[PDB]
Amino acid sequence: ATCELALENKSLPGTVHAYVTGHEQGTDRWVLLRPDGSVYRPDSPGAPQTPLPVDCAIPLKGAGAGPVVMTLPQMYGARVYFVRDDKLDFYLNPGPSLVEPAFATPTDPNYGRTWSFCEFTFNPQQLYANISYVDLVTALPIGLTLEGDSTHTVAPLPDGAVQRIADDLTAQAASDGQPWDKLVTRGSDGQVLRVVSPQNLMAPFFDRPDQMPFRDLFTAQIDEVWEKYRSTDLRIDLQGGRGTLAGRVSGDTLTFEGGHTFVKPTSKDIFTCNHGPFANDPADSDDKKALLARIAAGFNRSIMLSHPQQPNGTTVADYYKGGVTNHWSRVVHANSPIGYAFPYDDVRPDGEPDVSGAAHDGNPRRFTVSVGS
Image (cartoon, rainbow, N blue to C red; front, side, top):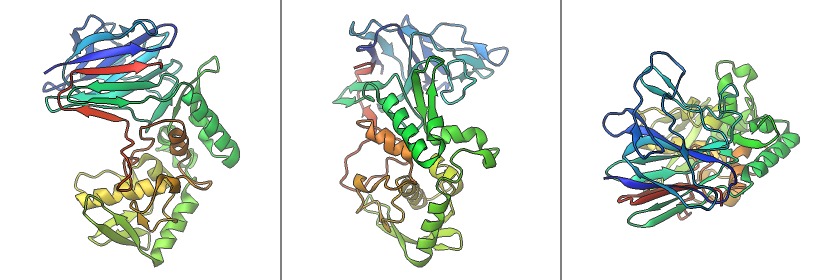
């Protein structure tokens, strides 16, 4: 099966190029869709940082001129990139390993460029696409529509969201002295290009935690939470009808019935949702993983003190209250109609709507990916 990929610039003046990158189903080989509709499968280069030998920039028709429509082959771990004005510099490392523009790396050739991407996978089961703000929001917000068995739309960041987000986070930084303002990337001309989530600002300092931004953002709150649940249960509803597991902090180990253990998180853990007690471990049981997700989510949303039982019984109104919270997620949620802003944002109270930025269809006919509005 293949699917139509429609690439659209709705409204933005100037030049927009799309890139489509992914792994070809089966071969696992990096592929790029080419402007001519064909696939470019890079060979492994003779040297690292080898510029992409083929220009895979797909020029979009002008604002409102309609979509570039190509045949999307099946591929996984795929991305649709957009870039304004410039093209993106993709490179090849031996492998071939596609060197993807690193939005949170200031040395990156594209760091000063206005670009964005969304993610998708297209296999014989489905096309699954995702607008996610876990890592960044950009001046080039992407929206998508997946037409197949049904029509699925994911609304983009509204025009100007990245500026609002940058401004809110800078305002936050003024208020709390935390480096929320450092999450903002401005081009050499002051244009807000993107704002990245805190883990992306923290990741360069993972090797040097003492200098890590936000290192102690959550430290006091975590101690408060850990202390709270030394003397009263934390009840985590695994949901899906699996029930709640009650946990108590034993020393520094949050331990649930069933033997699930969570060492005291750090601010790093809370932001990445993937270190300390939130480190993904494939050996983890489903329950452990469900517990992990919900605990990380509750820390990010700062409901660990307010809600000894969660996520059921909590609402979005409970999230992100007080000075110490994942303000990135709070601000992105305030400035986005849909889509997750942190890795366990999919944790939601039963009966609350899916606010993922995902669209998926088992019989995709057209995947329309658009910038502008």
